[PDB]
Length: 234
Figure 1 (cartoon, rainbow, N blue to C red):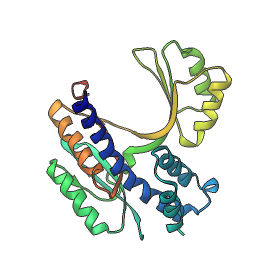
Figure 2: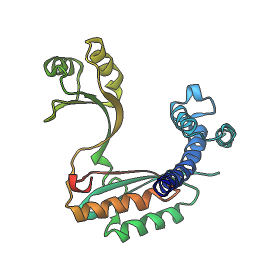
Figure 3: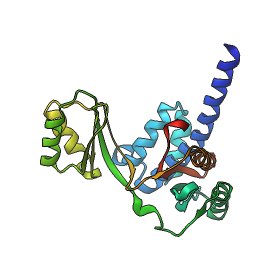
Figure 4: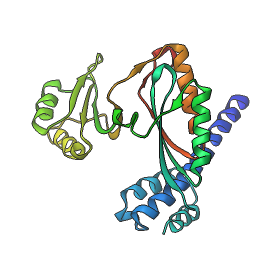
């Protein structure tokens, strides 16, 4: 009861704090890059929506916007982790020398290391991913996907269908599906890995730890990897 709930709220609060700090920086940088007008700045639109969803105070949001008009810079690190998993770490920082050392330390603690710019980035692409539930019309989805230039269609053991698209074709293809009364369970543009690296329980635990260490840094915005985690650690 109270023990589990207070402990649960404590964790939920602690994560809200870390995310708060990341959002502030992303608001500021999005504003500085794409401008102060949220309606003409999709990047800013997205983070401001996330900020309001997280109940960040309006004044904190607006001041973060006005600050972009901090000396935060974008930096990407690329490296390898347990079992040679490729890892990309996107950062917003006012001190790259501080950040790179902290990122190296995390990688090093998990038997990994940073490589050169471009050493892994080619494995990771933004892709539209439209997911249809079991009992969807496989045939009709396939017909539309070929007609409209989908990158891939995968039918899973449970009957669910995942359609992957180039980011630029995402909206059109989603619209084509809905027009044919094919209603997706979920659709988004996300980052997908071209190849994956299968992990045993132990390596998976170490990779999870690495992800967690990196995300705990205020300088880190997003961590991507091509790890294929086993069901045992899930």
